[PDB]
Structures are given as C-alpha cells and as structure tokens.
Image: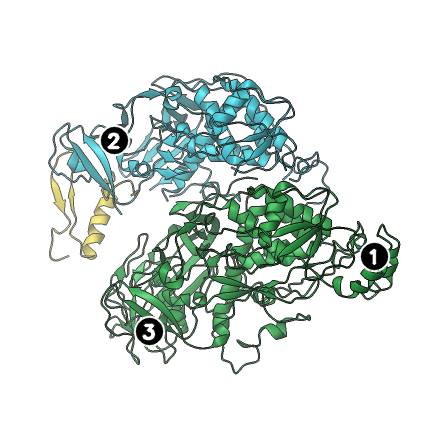
Chain colours: A green, B cyan, C yellow
Amino acid sequence: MSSLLNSLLPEYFKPKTNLNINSSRVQYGFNARIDMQYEDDSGTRKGSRPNAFMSNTVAFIGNYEGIIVDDIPILDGLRADIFDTHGDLDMGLVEDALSKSTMIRRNVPTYTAYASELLYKRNLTSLFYNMLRLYYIKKWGSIKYEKDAIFYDNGHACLLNRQLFPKSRDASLESSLSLPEAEIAMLDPGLEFPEEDVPAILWHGRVSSRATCILGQACSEFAPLAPFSIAHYSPQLTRKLFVNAPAGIEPSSGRYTHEDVKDAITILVSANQAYTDFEAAYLMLAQTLVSPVPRTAEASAWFINAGMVNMPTLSCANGYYPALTNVNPYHRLDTWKDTLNHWVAYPDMLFYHSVAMIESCYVELGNVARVSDSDAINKYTFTELSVQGRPVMNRGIIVDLTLVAMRTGREISLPYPVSCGLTRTDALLQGTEIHVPVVVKDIDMPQYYNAIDKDVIEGQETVIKVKQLPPAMYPIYTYGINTTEFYSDHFEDQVQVEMAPIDNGKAVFNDARKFSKFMSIMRMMGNDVTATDLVTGRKVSNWADNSSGRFLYTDVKYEGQTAFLVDMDTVKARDHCWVSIVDPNGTMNLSYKMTNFRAAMFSRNKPLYMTGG
Amino acid sequence: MSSLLNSLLPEYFKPKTNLNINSSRVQYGFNARIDMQYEDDSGTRKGSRPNAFMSNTVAFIGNYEGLTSLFYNMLRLYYIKKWGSIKYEKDAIFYDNGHACLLNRQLFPKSRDASLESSLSLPEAEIAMLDPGLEDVPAILWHGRVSSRATCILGQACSEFAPLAPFSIAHYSPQLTRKLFVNAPAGIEPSSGRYTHEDVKDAITILVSANQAYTDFEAAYLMLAQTLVSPVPRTAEASAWFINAGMVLSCANGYYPALTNVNPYHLDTWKDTLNHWVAYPDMLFYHSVAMIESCYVELGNDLLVAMRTGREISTEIHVPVVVKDIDMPQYYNAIDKDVIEGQETVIKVKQLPPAMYPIYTYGINTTEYSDHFEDQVQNLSYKMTNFRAAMFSRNKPLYMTGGSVRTIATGNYRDAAERLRA
Amino acid sequence: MAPIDNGKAVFNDARKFSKFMSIMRMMGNDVTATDLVTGRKVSNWADNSS
C-alpha cells in the first residue's frame, strides 16, 4: 500500500524521483538550529549551533532465510458474474460461464469437476516479490561488500562483518547471485486433464526473448555468497511454469537490463488482473530492503540469529480457465490499482518508504521491550488485541503494520488479511540472554560493558551479555508527532539540577528521569560527563553514540537502584560549537529550542543529493 | 525559481536585459547620500557626505568538485561559449590590504594560465538511435530530426569535465553516462564538432518541451545560481571559507512514450523559470549575486535565505599569506613574530568572520551590522537617501545594455476550481 | 564592538571612556589604555583609597 507508507514521511520532506545510490551505507537525517542556554546564580551562558545533524545509519546487509508457507487465496481479479451476493465462488455459475465460452466441448465436464480445487489457488505474491528483487539487483549492482570491514565501532568495543556473517566471501551485488533458469513450457489448449502442482499464467500476445530469461530466474533458488538484503536465501518456487500464450514462447536470451523487468511485471499484472497480489509483494520488500546499523554496541542482539521470511507458495490456475478473467473484474476497494501505478511512475521512492517502516518498527520495539509480563498489553499479547480481522497466523506484515499503527496513532486498513513477509519480534519473545561477539580496542572496556572477562588485553575476541534489548534506532522521521518521555524528542525541554555551595561540585541524582535529561542536554552542549553508580560501582558515559547525539537510559546496561554520583570538576569540552561550564555554584537550569528543519542525506562521508522531477 | 530570486533584489533597482562581462572580477554597490548631525558637551556640528560608494567584490574563481544533471551541464556549456574570453593569470592578486597579500598560486595549486574556452577540451559520448521494436542507459524524446549541432552538445554535456584553470562554471564533474538513446522518428545526423552559444538555447528549448521536464530545469537553474560566482573576501581572515574544496542521470520517456501525453500532472506556475531564462539569459548573474550574498551574510551570525528575508520559502584554519610590510605580525595573528618583506608565512583563524556586507539586502531587516537608513548612536544622527546602483569592472564603469525587462509571471489558477492543498 | 575587531576598541568620546575605566576597577580588572595621537599610557589603578 503506497498510500499508508507515504503518510509516514515528514511534512518538510519534499522527495524527487531519482536517487543515485553508490554505496552500502546511507546516513539519512535532518539539519536543525539548536539555541542552548545555561542559567546559574552567577549568570547566563548562551550558545547556538546553526547546523546540527541528527542521523540514523542504514545499510544494505542483513541475514534473512525464506520458507514456503500456506496462505489464504486472493479472489480479486476473477469476473464479477460467478460471485454470489455474500462474495464467494457460487459453483453452478462457473459451469454456466465455461459452457457459454470458446472452450473445447469434450473438456467442459472434466475441467468443471477440477474447478472446486483449482479456482482457490490464486496467490502470485512470491513471483512478484522475486521479480522486484531482480529489478534492484541490476539497478544498484555496483555496490560492494568487504569481508574485513567495520560493522560497528564506538571507540571502546569494535564489531567486524566476519563476526556476525561467517561463510561470507567479499564480492559485488551483481557478482553475488548465479541464478539457474527454470523451464517455461507452452500450455497446449487441448490437454485432457489439468496438471495440479504446476502453475499456469496468462500473457498478452508473444512472450519476448528477455521475458523468458526473467520468469526463468524469478522461479529459481537464490544461493548468495555475500549477505545482501535484496539477495537473501529463497527456496525454489516451482520446477516448471506453463504460459497460455497462443503466440509461441521465444527461447531464453541470457542477458537483460533493469528496464526489461518493469516490462515483464506490467504485462503479468494486466493479463492476470493481480493488483492486490502486487500490493502484498510491495509491503513485503519494504520490510526487507534495508536493515539498520545498531545505535549502540549492545544493540546488535536483534541481528545475531537469522529472521525467517514467510513467502506464500506459488499457485495460479488462470492458464486452464481463460474465460473466467475478463475486463469486468471483482474488487473490494475502489483504489486497488494505486500501488502498481505509484511504483511504475517512481521506482526509487521504495527506499524512502522502506526506511520509514523499519524506523517506525524498531522505535516501538524499543519501548515495548521495557514493559513487565504481568500486564494487559505486554510483550506476548500486543498483536492479538490490535488485530480486528481473521488472519491464518499473527506473523509477517500483521506484526509490522500493528507497530506502525501504535507509532503514528492511526487505523491501518488492508483489503485481505494476508500474513506474509519478515517477522522481527524473534529475539524479544525468546526472553533469554544473547551472547554478541566483540573485538576490544582499549584495556579498560569491561567496567562500561557487561563483559564475560574482567581483564582483557587489546585485540582479544570477547563476549558481551545483553539481557534487556536497547533501542536499535532513534526517532528522526517520526520526531515530535507522538512524543514519549523515554526518548524525550520534544522541540522545547528544560532540567533543574539543585546544588548548594557547601557541596564541592558533587551532585547525587536520586531521580532517574531528570538524570537522563541532564546527561543528554550536556552532550548537545559538547561536554563529556562520566557518572559512577554508588550501589553497584559501575560507570556510564553520555558519549555512547556518534549519530543521534542523545543519551537514552538503556545506556546504563543495568536495572537496579538509582544513585548516580556526577563530579562537576571532571567535565571535559570534546566537540566544537559548545557552551563552557568553568565552575558552577548554586542551582543550574539547562534548556534548548529546535526552530527549523531541512532534510539531508550522507554517503561515503559526502552529501547525497536528490535529482529528477 | 525566478520569482523567488527576483524578489531578493532591492525595490529601486530594475536591471536591463544584456550585460557584457569582460573580466573575472565585478564590483556592485550603490551611490547613497548621508546627512550626519553631531552633538556633544562642547557644542553642535552639522555636515553632509554628497556621494558615498558602498560595494562588495564578486569573482568567477572557486574550487569545486562533483534530468537535472543533464540541464546543469547544458547551462554551463552556454556560459563557457558566451563569456569565453575571461583570462586567469596565476601570478595575480586575490586579496590586497597593504600589510598582507594572497596570490592565486596560493589557495589554487595545480593550476596554469588559460582562457575559459581554452580550460576544457571535452570528449563526446555515443548518441545512438533507439529503433522502435526493441522489447543503466537513459532514453529521451525529441521534436523531428536531431540537428548536426544538437548531437555535439548532448555528446559533450554527458562527458567528463577536467579543467586546467580554477573557474566556477568549469568545475570538475564525473561522467554522467556512456550512451544516451534518442527516440527520434527521423534518424540523427553525425556530430559536427563546432557549435555557437545560440545553438545551445535551441537544444535546451526542444529537450524540455518534448520530455515535459520543466521542474527538472528549475532545480538546475537554482543549482547553478549557487556555483556561478564566488565572493572576494572582505578581510584576509575571510579566505578560510574557500581553502577546502566544497562538494557539488536516469529517464524512461524514450522507451514508453505513452506515459508522456497532452495532459501532464503538475504548482500552476511550473513553466515560469524556463520562460524567464529563454527571454533574459544574462539575468542569472544578478540572481546568483543576490543568493550568495544572502548566504554568506547570515553565516556571519542555502534556501539561510529564509533567515535573511524573514519569509516562508516553498579546528583553527591555516590561511597562507605573503608579507608586504615589515610590521605585519603586530596586526595579524602570524606564526613567525619576526618577518621580512617577501617571506611567505601563515596566519591563524579560529572564528570565521563575515565574507560579505549587506548591499542588495540593506535595511530589509536590521541586526545590531547596524545597516539602518536612520539611526541615533549614543550623539550622531544620520539619514541615508538617493540610492542608485552602479557596477565597476577592471577599474572602469560597467554599463548595462539592451532594453527594459518586461514582467513574465502566471497566476495561482489557470482554470482550476478548488485548491487541493496537497 | 563588532566581532571583526579582535578585542581592540577606540573611544572617540571622553565621557564614556571615564565611566568604562572606573566601573572596570570596581570589578577588579587592571586596564592599560594607550593614546594614539601623543603615544602616552594611562592606568585605571592610580589610587588605593576611593
């Protein structure tokens, strides 16, 4: 659905058609003007950063694995005459329709008997999904993946691509896949009895030399070398595929450009009258196009084990019954062609729709992981109460759309309750410890991170124990539309730290809420604060990120009693465009204001500009 | 966006069509009249400055690195041919106060002496014909037969730009494409080799009309307004901006011409920017000066223009310097505290000073710059009247030629009933 | 003063020069001005009583 994914984009964001991606990493964000202020008994110290960049790093890598599952049939496309008043295939009008057609008279009785099974095999979502992936593989084919590259680095802990993805050879996206071609046979109209477990599709005129090569590779096994997101592992959809084209199928060309795949899709949707099937395939790819680079080192727990993609079995019986498809189809919603028409016009807009969906999900799974099991709407039972339909199983797109509904705070409506796509909530529902690997840089690491060893020499491969999952992304596109006090994504905010002159700079934060806001605003002002917990004896640093530049409370990496000693004569000025706290006395009052917003994107440490219409 | 950048010019100034630029440096300002009145404890004194010239200096020198991208290069080819007699000398002055001096050897190493036409030697990309029947190469529509001259322009527009002299409209750009299909019913002619600046206008006007790429042109027009000219710094410290080099094609109309028909989807003022350029090409110079002034003024405190006008639009740096007088270390924050006339030293810049003073945007909104018309400083009370724009080029007056610019502009509605806000 | 000036201020008026130099001494700051015409120097710390 192009419509609901379009509304997620910000108001200030004015997108153009073409986006020239030339790398496997993009820093999308915005430039804002922050007017910071520090008030005290001595006096006020004002600062102003005219261009402050808040970013979320998004990559084209992510381990996924496809499995063939059984899903509901999509009945949109068939002629409106055969349907009854309620909206189900009234068999008796089918026998009437086949009799008054251009069919062979000896086949009518034998074909009508099979109709009861074959007419309820209508799901082309798997074919459109694979054909969409072939379009983007050939378009952005020049992107590279290096084996010994930096997946994450925060100074203390480093995580390489070798650690997360073993069995991985370095290669370009174009050179990753070597797809073998499936047989595309021509359907004989004078066949005695239809062959079930072999799908037959319709076509307009002659199947071109390039269309054979595309359909051949779409219905085949994806066995990748490099762990790319649009070239993940998928099983063999089918062995043979019939095509009811009176004009003969030309033999396989071998080569094809990305423009020839658009030609193949537009003919297939038009002939078969399968627009709702395409809408399902569009939302499936929107989830699994780009995966987020983790915000913190301990936020890599989401991407350790491979999340399963639910691809519905390829099943189509239009080739055997050409009469039942015509120019007057049955459809539920009137705006049923809108998703295809949007893709044909603006193909590259899917990148913006993809980041909008994953940013909406991973933000909400951040503040869903921080609720106790003893509650009404909790970790296990947040999907059931929200869903007001009849899906086969609460997985795939249903779990991702219900998280978007919670974020925006609106009612999302689909025509068919289809349950296909990636399932994200895997590591959450397990509710166990996850062991993420890390290579150390400094020697004073295991004070900050909950490491397995207490003394570790530099260049050693260690393990961090992550219990509660921290947020993987910070809200940027959904900034101050449905604000919560956890993220604290306000335009205006203030904090009042109360100290007396008798105290020699040392302040104890009994409250957890205002400790988070103090540590966050001090980082906007470019000050490196290092607090120490009095009960446990661990340490936390506000500089635990190089993208957003905010401090979330999950950076403590421990749930206990709140007694944070901060010494305010060890505050160090780190960044440029900063206000100085030389020597405070009395009550401190910090405050900021974000005034205007301008969309900005970065790639290879250079500006990435939007071009076209 | 013509109507946006046209608004930035002052209400009194209305420039003429043509402007014969014959140098790499242009002063622009106004001749105002100041009526001062002084009062203190000793007594009162009244005077009057009859003619006072307040001006900035803007140049065609700026180190930069690289269907909107195609129109961008086609526009750059137009101005290379038109103003293709501007000389860049390597051992010339960039800034000169009296104590310090910056040469063009410094700020621009890896440069030689060349004219603007002699800077680029562009190769030609293959312009092939798309035969109808074929079932990372763009295809564009065309009206009738592709002319012998039109081939050479499209060929050079797609090719790599590799300059010798640092010029603003000849900056380094990567190769757009290798091939470019043209769905022309009549076959294309082979490339001639030579073309006039007038022939590039004919190429742009046809390419936009056929493809209906009016909004793509508007993007390229604004994109060139930033690059076209660069500021000459106000003081020696304001050279810190221009040390590090600032960083600056797909179409499927040829394949599927059914998608582009007689009823296109569009603002109702979506053909104004092209209609403005095709009528008055030399007006871009004034729009460019207006834009780069607004940006570099507000950075002292791109679409910075909103912060300037106040309307809704829809590490220490090591500057290399030359010592002219022996007493230089007293004024500038120099590394070597003892110097000799001729020595090349380096000065330190921590906070970036303003590169330009408000001239066109003088008194539209006054900050405490203190660019008032009337002000009482505490006692000095002055009044500014009788503004008249004047431009100087190569220490002589540069006069505007041609006729008076008549307004072209379309209303918010043609025959549209309801404003579907969108 | 403007940011273009690197701390250096010239007092054309004699009245406000006297008030600046006096209030800076209440604040406990040792200012040393130099006359541009003659080339002599004046210090605000020229008394230990008032």
Report whether B26 appears left or right of B400.
Answer: left
Disc 2 is placed on an element classified as loop
Q: Which mark is residue A450?
A: 3
**CB atoms of marks 2 and 3 within 8 Å:** no
Mark 2 → mark 3, Cα distance in angstroms = 53 Å
Element carrying mark 3: loop
As displayed, is residue B232 above or below residue B306? above
From the viewer's perspective, is residue A223 above or below residue B170? Answer: below
Identify residue type, mark 1.
Asn
**Identity of the residue drawn at 65% across and 50% down:** A184
Q: Nearer the viewer, mark 1 or mark 3?
A: 1
Image position, residue C27 (x, y; %) = 21, 57
Say whether marks 1 and 3 touch (CB < 8 Å). Answer: no
Q: Nearer the viewer, mark 1 or mark 2?
A: 1
Residue located beneath label 2 in the image: B106
- Report whether residue A309 is seen: yes
Residue A394 lies in quadrant? bottom right
Tell me where residue B363 appears, x and y as whole percent.
44, 37
Toward the viewer: A315 or A460?
Answer: A315
Q: Residue furthest front?
A: A192
Q: Chain of mark 1?
A: A
Above-or-below relation of B350 to A467: above
Disc assigned to residue A107? 1
Label 1 – label 2 distance at C-alpha: 88 Å
Observer-nearest of A282 and A477: A282
Q: Position of residue B158 (x, y in %)?
A: 48, 30
Q: Quadrant of the N terminus of chain B?
A: top right
Which amino acid lies under the numbered mark 2 shown in the image of this protein? Answer: Gln
